[PDB]
Image (tube, helix red, strand yellow):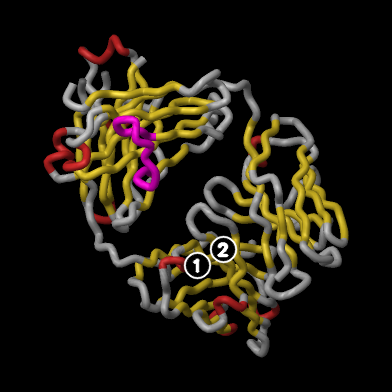
Amino acid sequence: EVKLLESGGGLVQPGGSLKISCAASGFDFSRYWMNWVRQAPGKGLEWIGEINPDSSTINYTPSLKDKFIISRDNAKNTLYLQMSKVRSEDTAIYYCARQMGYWGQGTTLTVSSASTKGPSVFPLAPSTAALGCLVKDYFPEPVTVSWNSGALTSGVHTFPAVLQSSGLYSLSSVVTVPSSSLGTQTYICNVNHKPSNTKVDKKVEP
Amino acid sequence: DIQMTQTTSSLSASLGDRVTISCSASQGISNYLNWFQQKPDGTVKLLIYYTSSLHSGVPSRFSGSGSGTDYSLTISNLEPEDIATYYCQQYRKLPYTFGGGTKLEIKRTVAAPSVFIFPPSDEQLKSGTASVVCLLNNFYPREAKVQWKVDNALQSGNSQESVTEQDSKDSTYSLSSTLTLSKADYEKHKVYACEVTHQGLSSPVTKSFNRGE
């Protein structure tokens, strides 16, 4: 099985640098041209560049040719991409590919000034009813939300986060429940932000 | 740069249908056209290379065709694993360029949203900011419009929204919009409303509250 395993992604401040890697296995790496491709949140695929087996030809998409350096180390079966002067627009998932036939799973670059911060959780109180939790001002992604420690799953929608202009994320989770249950049934949203080690249980009522 | 155009960005289908996705190039690309599938988890696979050669591992229900400028991917009978986004790519001239993508989804009957408005909590207001939330629950099709109004002033530039992925059980979408104001702006006004337009509503639905009532 052809396998391509990326690593080296993370948080980087604007103007910083990062080198990402792609470790190949299950084929003869030294025999192939390799490609890098990226995808910004909610956008399409964009080609970055290609390198031939002996590194004598390296082709870049013209807009990135000064920013980015592709290289490879055949003895190590690894392909590299060096990113410099990164900006917000470079925030993306970065994929390696053997030609365009086999793709890595991706590693993520987030370019941001924001510091790690756990969310504030606010109620979206009911008054079929809907209720929810607003999970506001955290960094970086992800957060997870359950209801009633996972006993409540039907009618739940946990929305994708939005990146606010502060550089911090905000998401909502909501559930629709019978109006008659409201006086009697307890509803607690369980929020876990692993990157800040923050857990909050928020009870929501009328 | 060769510009690749997939002029349908969203395409509805039923399980078992033949589906066709179209791509066109801004100038001739001599059959150097790849098709990619990106699944919901983000995994990318090559399906078809050189216009019509099936990549190893790909079932023959996928096929491709075309030349010069115009190309199509056909899925002969849609399976649930095929609900994904498809991108074309030309590799005739550097830089290689991709289409904007076509996302498949499942057709069902039109269903109007249930709409709910949520005032900001007193807890949040203590910190100096008010978030007002509008929820549009279980609608189809995906296209919907929310307009915020504060004492009849249309609000623009001070909301954000996001939409769930198509539900696996009922094939609907839900949407959440948040309007953000300072506490000081929030307390200067009374009537807060979200007005929702959608194909299932014969005219727009407004949900509103009066602050402090």
- Return the residue nearer the eye: B48 or B65: B65
Nearest the eye: A12 or B43: A12
Q: Amino acid at mark 2?
A: Gly
Residue on which disc 1 sits? A6
Pointer 1 local density, CA inside 10 Å: few below 14, some 14–19, many at least 20: many
Is B60 located above or below residue A19 in the figure? above
SS label for mark 1: strand
Q: Secondary structure at mark 2?
A: loop
- Residue A162 appears at what percent x and percent y? 38, 48
Quadrant including the N terminus of chain B: bottom right
Q: Where is B30 relative to B105, above or below? A: below
Q: Position of residue A72 (x, y in %)?
A: 57, 82
**Residue numbers of the magenta segment:** B148-159
- Residue B171 is situated, as x and y percent measured from the top left of the image, at 56, 28
Residue at mark 2 shares a chain with residue at mark 1? yes
Residue drawn at 29 percent across, 31 percent down: B151
**Is B157 covered by the magenta stretch?**
yes
Task: Confirm or deny contact between disc 2 and disc 1 (CB under 8 A).
Answer: yes
The amino acid marked with disc number 1 is Glu
Q: Which residue is mark 2?
A: A104
* Chain ID of residue with mark 2: A
Residue located at (83% from left, 55% from top):
B70
